[PDB]
Length: 140
Image (cartoon, one colour):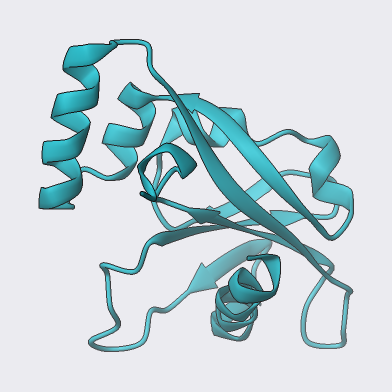
């Protein structure tokens, strides 16, 4: 889980560059866009610097306390938000349709790994957050 999302976090760390008070992430050519993760990068103060996808409901669901340490956490969000997160994913969209019909405020829980990268000569201190886009309720 955490140990598993750590790999994606490390990847995005090595992909990132710090230039002119800004994070830039250049994605590798032909990289899978269909991986079930979304990564966010914050500064040590907890300011969001970069996000793989701009999804405000999920971003607002990230608790600031979490951001100062390494940890494994859970987002408690809604089926509307999860549907926005999984928009491109066809099959998932079918399932999501179903669940939306049974309950329109159905709760969705997403695993999250928070990862700390101390400042180096190359890079300032960063917190990298990796979210499992498939919620616990849909894993089975």
